[PDB]
């Protein structure tokens, strides 16, 4: 919708309800992903490359604490290549990484705020 | 009037290996 309406505050309030905390949810950004190659923060490198055993950020954030709320702040700024991964996060509820382990988002909450419109009905 | 009969022994210590971890250079 518009700016300043409090979308992120609604998400933090929702996380405040069913956790009695406010920082246990998983916020990431979509403003740091303006180029093509930074997709691999949330996957991990294939076998043979520099950071391999460390794993993915978004993947490791769910193998522990598998009940989080996941945010995507201002998902417009990412040029249309990050969208190919959350095309398959949704509707299957799985994602894989370098090790071939399969995380499962089958009881998480996906909340992805946007910024478009802003003046129309 | 017994003897000594100096017995033998066997030794072992293995080796390591390294991995190179190429960098994609962009
Ligand atoms: N409907 C609302 N109920 C209660 N507080 C609100 C409401 N809307 C806004 N606020 C307050 O006003 C502030 C701004 O709301 P936010 O949700 O933080 O803005 P925002 O959605 O992050 O805007 P952008 O576009 O991301 S910069 C928050 O700190 C809220 O506490």
Image (cartoon, coloured by chain):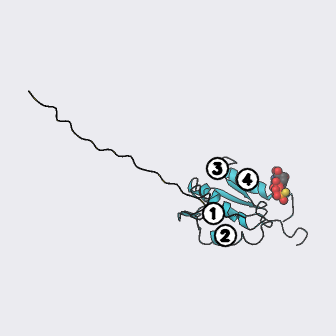
Chain colours: A cyan, B yellow
Nearest to viewer (mark 3 / mark 1): 1
Please report the residue visible at 27 percent of the width from the left and 41 percent of the height from the top: B9
Left or right of residue B20: residue A5: right
- Secondary element type, mark 1: loop
Q: Residue at x 21, y 38 (%)?
A: B7
Upstream in sequence: badge 3 or badge 1: 3
On-image quarter of the C terminus of chain B: bottom right
State the separation of the CA atoms marked 1 and 4. 25 Å
Mark 3 nearby-residue class (10 Å; few <14, some 14–19, many ≥20) = few
Which residue is labeled 4 in the image? Answer: A12
Residue under label 3, please give it. A19
The answer to whether residue B1 is above or below residue A35 is: above
Q: Chain of mark 3?
A: A
Residue nearest the observer in this picture, A77 or A27: A77
Which residue is nearer to you in this view: B17 or A106? B17
Compare marks 2 and 1 and give the one earlier in the sequence.
1
Image coordinates for residue A4, horizontal then vertical, percent = 86, 57
CB within 8 Å, label 3 to label 4: no
Q: Image quadrant of residue A61? A: bottom right
The numbered dot on residue A85 is 2
Q: Decide which of tag 3 and tag 4 comes sooner along the chain.
A: 4
Q: Is mark 2 within 8 Å of ligand 1?
A: no
Chain of the residue displaying label 1: A
């Amino acid at each position: 919708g518009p700016t300043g309406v409090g979308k992120t505050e609604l998400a933090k309030a929702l996380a405040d309800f069913l956790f009695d905390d406010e920082r246990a949810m998983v916020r990431i950004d979509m403003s740091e992903y303006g180029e093509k190659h930074t997709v691999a923060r949330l996957i991990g490198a294939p076998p043979g490359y520099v950071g391999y055993e460390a794993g993915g950020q978004l993947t490791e954030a769910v193998r522990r604490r598998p009940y989080t709320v996941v945010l995507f702040d201002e998902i417009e700024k990412a040029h249309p290549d990050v969208f190919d991964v959350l095309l398959q996060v949704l509707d299957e509820g799985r994602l894989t990484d370098g090790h071939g382990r399969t995380v499962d988002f089958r009881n998480t909450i996906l909340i992805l705020t946007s910024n478009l419109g802003s003046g129309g009905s | 009037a017994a003897a000594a009969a100096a017995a033998a022994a066997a030794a072992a210590a293995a080796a390591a290996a390294a991995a190179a971890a190429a960098a994609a250079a962009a």
